Image (cartoon, rainbow over the protein chains, first blue to last red):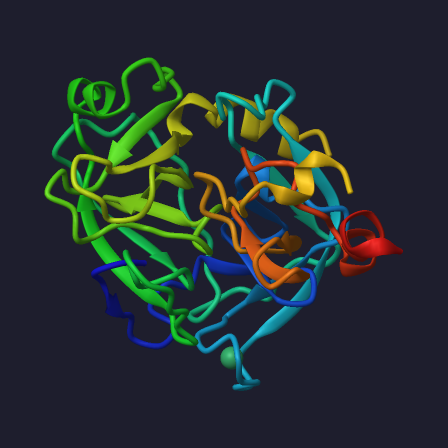
Length: 223
Length: 58
Ligand SMILES: [Ca+2]
């Protein structure tokens, strides 16, 4: 996360780390046995790290659970990045409460201006490279489809929303993918893509989670 | 070596932190980098062995 701050330990109970040997993506626990992430973060074997804070030190509060099933959206487009969503089923239910908690699905889509929280262990530098051991947080508002589409002419589908600041300086970055964008206690976005990081007029584009509640419920309730 | 061994490295526009190897045409050796998971180029191999085979001479 670029231009953000270190979150208080275990302040984001729903944030999970995706591991295949090292941290490659993020995610959010929607229910004790399912995790939501991005489709481009797909891998055949993935371990979900719950209750994490400092991904480099065994602190004692973490839960290491392996994925039992991995489901990417049927219509994921590797080129346009449309439908960048993926569901991972844990092989064992996560032991919930306090440091490990689920995030609520959207009851309504978020409107432009709504303030959200974006968290992750991604790059903190918009220019150079720097990866935090500690979880970073960022408060950013949902932009309007207008600004988003002007920022990326011909590249914004109805399944994407720009969250960020057109003046740059703050944004998500490499390592944050699959991560959570939570506004008013509901999960509204998944860190997807963007031209660079924290660049001016190039906000971050996220998978619009409200366009998939029905699909998510059905998939979970049938797997 | 195929033409793609001379393409510069490209992480892409996605924000994933995926370890992959590319042939550094400057240092003339395969190296490690981080692919975002989408829209890169052919100078992107899943293992260092593969890379050394195609671009170095294995
Ligand atoms: Ca730790």
